[PDB]
Image 1 (cartoon, rainbow over the protein chains, first blue to last red):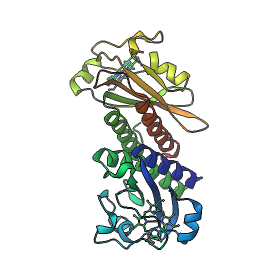
Image 2 (image 1 turned 180 degrees about the horizontal axis):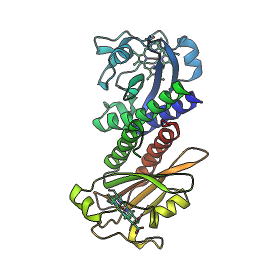
Image 3 (image 1 turned 90 degrees about the horizontal axis):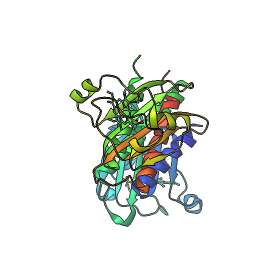
Image 4 (image 1 turned 60 degrees about the vertical axis):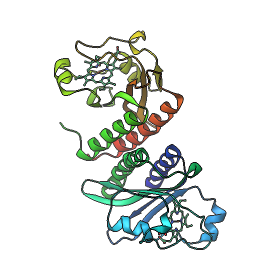
Length: 144
Length: 148
Ligand code: HEM
Ligand code: HEM
């Protein structure tokens, strides 16, 4: 199961960096969402928010132009679309592409590092390393 | 022959992250087949001249052979003092502190991720072990899904 694998990767990222929230989106070449896995938000809150992300705002930027991005305040970025009603507040941000050499498929991202600090150089390196493993997983599912 | 390019980049990045974050002087990973024969070995922290002097890659013996045989996390204050120790070959850096963990999925283990010589002179911490285990699990995912 691909989503179980992607969830394991999100868990490792969130726990090791010590972020409150973690997520991964995988999309097709038209930018349609194929998979969205996440941790940090209870299902009651999920039910209030409603539909899962479509890959807009800051995530849209990263889908169009895959490369690592860290932000002190996600809502301050020019590409920021804003959260939907009932979504938890989130401030600090780290996002990296989920990719292989040939192609990028998705984005692994974290918000709200514990105790309020920005994501570090070391956090970005770690998250890139985990994402690469997810990149291989996604590339394999696309063949198999 | 050579490892799949994406797999190799991923494993090397994982070794680097593990080595960097636990502040190890040296880091390595061996990957083996189902019969436990070593196929690939990637490493960092040893200069290229010392590599030429050592002259042959590890076969998976000593304390590593133990981890290959019995895939479990293993921390040691002095790797050379372990009764499984085979000893380092000529020209190989002396290495004292050791942290090694299986590269695996639920059903099968594929290899070992290992770090030596913490910069602080101290043994690898419990925190160090947890971080390396998670990185090894991602390496396990990579190996399992790697391009045929
Ligand atoms: C738990 C991990 C999550 C993280 C780290 C996260 C993070 C984000 C980020 C960074 C944005 C872009 C904000 C902006 O551009 O201003 C966003 C937008 C959004 N999020 Fe969340 N989110 C998470 C979970 C969820 C969940 C579970 C839902 C739905 C139940 C959700 C629904 C949305 C929607 C609808 C948007 C608007 C843009 C879009 O549709 O892509 N998010 N989120
Ligand atoms: C740079 C990261 C490295 C680490 C962390 C590392 C670690 C180790 C450890 C823990 C042992 C077992 C010691 C014992 O059981 O007494 C060992 C043995 C050995 N190492 Fe290294 N090593 C590294 C690099 C290298 C390189 C680059 C070479 C060759 C160019 C090499 C060649 C060997 C050989 C030949 C053995 C003897 C046992 C065997 O053949 O498996 N090592 N190493």
